[PDB]
Amino acid sequence: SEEPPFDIRALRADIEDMISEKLELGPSLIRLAWHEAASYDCFKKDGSPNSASMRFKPECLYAGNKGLDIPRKALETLKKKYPQISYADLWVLAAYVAIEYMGGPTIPFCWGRVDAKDGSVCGPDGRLPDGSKTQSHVREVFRRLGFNDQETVALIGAHTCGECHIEFSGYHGPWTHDKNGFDNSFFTQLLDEDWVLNPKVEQMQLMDRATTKLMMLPSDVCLLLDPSYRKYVELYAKDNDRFNKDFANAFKKLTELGTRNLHKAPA
Ligand code: HEM
Ligand SMILES: [Ca+2]
Ligand SMILES: [K+]
Image 1 (cartoon, helix red, strand yellow):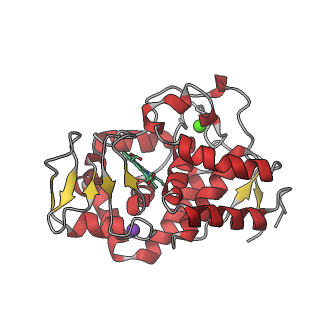
Image 2 (tube, protein in one colour):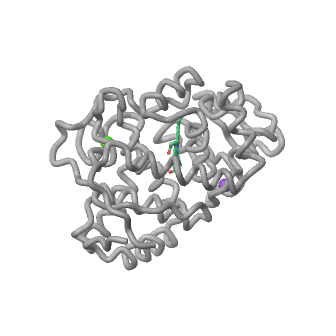
């Protein structure tokens, strides 16, 4: 109900077209917006979330952000065509477009994020979660961000799409049988499969006994091990509509952390 100064309808279509040419970009755009928000610390009120601060060294070089230069570079062409949008809004909008385009919820978008002007606003390394660790670590990070256990589990559900790359994280493979689809299947797979050690990946990960084509990280399976998290894994595995709703709300919350003076965009 407040029109942004950029042509948002044309921009959403251009993002969909870009993804249509390179489907794997869809999940990386989600990972980009999440990691741009994940630098927050809600107690220190620092880390410049949702400000495209990851455009600056040192934050672009943190291990947890490896490979995110690919979606950032793809979005440059659109920034040149739509100069009135900030990078920060562009990264968020592209993630929302990607989510919907892969069959996920249509998340109400607010615009007006202001880009970080220099790298002095960047928070320290160590803010991003580490897939080799488990629930004590995951809960520490998500509590730092300001999320509860319900919201933590819903958000990790984004692993429904995309895959790990050895050159970026040292892990390998998709989590689900359709890495291009956004739904509750991460939770379905986590709950329904027998997760066995993958013998051939040097960084410890699990694979499904049934096909061996799926993967889970230590940080994924901790959602089954921790009784508080497991309740939500079960909730989402049996109720895709609840998953879509809860993911929308939490991801919207995530991409609005540390922001001010935002405006509702037209749907
Ligand atoms: C415990 C918390 C999390 C951990 C430890 C974690 C870890 C990882 C790792 C290791 C990768 C592989 C990166 C690569 O090799 O390309 C990855 C990818 C990905 N992550 Fe997460 N993640 C977490 C939470 C989240 C959240 C909250 C979201 C979004 C809401 C998210 C969205 C994605 C997506 C979409 C990919 C696929 C990227 C691609 O296909 O290029 N993750 N994550
Ligand atoms: Ca940031
Ligand atoms: K999927």
